[PDB]
Image: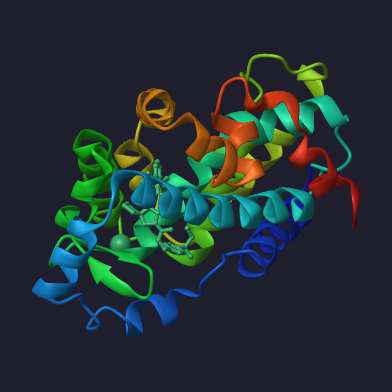
Amino acid sequence: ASLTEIEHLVQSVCKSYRETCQLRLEDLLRQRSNIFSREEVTGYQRKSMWEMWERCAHHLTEAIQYVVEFAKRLSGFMELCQNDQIVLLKAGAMEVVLVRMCRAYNADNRTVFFEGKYGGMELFRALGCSELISSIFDFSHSLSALHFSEDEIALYTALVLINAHRPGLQEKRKVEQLQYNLELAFHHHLCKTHRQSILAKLPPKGKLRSLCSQHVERLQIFQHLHPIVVQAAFPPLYKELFSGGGEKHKILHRLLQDS
Ligand SMILES: CCS(=O)(=O)c1ccc(CNC(=O)N2CC3(CCCC3)c3nc(-c4c(OC)ncnc4C4CC4)ccc32)cc1
Ligand code: NA
């Protein structure tokens, strides 16, 4: 590579993110004052466990859809073979959402954006997975302290997804080359903006893997309680990425084909 080529990659990644960020940061901050009432928290707590799981599975899917769109728009992703594209999204799309989540987290009152308003851990008690919720919250709290810029998230999420270590990749060297360019792009931006300090403060890759495995773990617990609910009321893309053996229907495949 060259210095010019690397700077072009920074802007290409940032553009790709701006176009696929789901909600604009400005729209998220303006809403921080809009918080659920005590009666509205009771309302969420009074809802059934299956209803809460269904609503949560639907929002995770919508967030994943934008992460798929980000991958398609990512420099060098569509050039990779179909197998590697799918391995990279199956293993990383969930992790990209988990990072993007801190944008909708307010560390001041310990609230997250959910269905038009801001709520705390209490709003998700009906789910019956208080450990996963607390984990998502602490992880969001941790990244909030870093005070990420939209460009920084754009470049970091690009690397999260483009990982050569992912098990099952056919063209490892091709991903190793893509990762190396994105590494440089990210490090160049951080160097230019005097933000090299956050590198040590970044969460270890093992923590992202832990939260993903924790989701699947609590999902199978819920699946054993309401199998017909996962079968009839859960999104097809969610089922493929997390439910076993819901991997039968290939939704990601069609998502990548068109455009
Ligand atoms: C993402 C791009 S963005 O533009 O910044 C953006 C856009 C929309 C929203 C709305 N909220 C939302 O989607 N929410 C809220 C919360 C956070 C914590 C509690 C509930 C949650 N959680 C999950 C989630 C999981 O998030 C990664 N991981 C595992 N399980 C779950 C489900 C609770 C079972 C999945 C969506 C989800 C927020 C942010
Ligand atoms: Na934040």
Whether 169 is drawn above or below 105: the answer is: above
Q: Please tell me how many numbered marks the rendered image carries.
A: 0
Colour convention: rainbow
Q: Residue at x 65, y 33 (%)?
A: 240
Residue 177 falls left or right of residue 13: right
The quadrant of the image that shows the N terminus is top right
Please name whichever residue, 223 or 111, is drawn nearer the observer in this view of the structure.
Answer: 223
Q: Residue at x 48, y 56 (%)?
A: 59
Locate residue 134: give its quadrant: top left
Quadrant for ligand 1?
bottom left
Query: Where residue 98 sits: x, y (%)?
Result: 43, 45
Q: Residue at x 46, y 62 (%)?
A: 193
Please name whichever residue, 96 or 187, is drawn nearer the observer in this view of the structure.
Answer: 96
Residue 143 falls left or right of residue 256: left
Locate residue 34: give its quadrant: bottom left
Residue 101 falls left or right of residue 20: left
Please name whichever residue, 228 or 145, is drawn nearer the observer in this view of the structure.
Answer: 228
Please name whichever residue, 244 or 30, is drawn nearer the observer in this view of the structure.
Answer: 244
Query: Where residue 216 sits: x, y (%)?
Result: 44, 27
Furthest-left residue in this view: 38
Regarding residue 250, the answer to whether it shows in the image is yes
Residue 209 falls left or right of residue 43: right
Regarding residue 177, the answer to whether it shows in the image is no
The quadrant of the image that shows the C terminus is bottom right
Q: Residue at x 72, y 55 (%)?
A: 69
Whether 228 is drawn above or below 138: the answer is: above
Query: Where residue 174 sits: x, y (%)?
Result: 81, 26
Query: Where residue 144 sits: x, y (%)?
Result: 27, 56
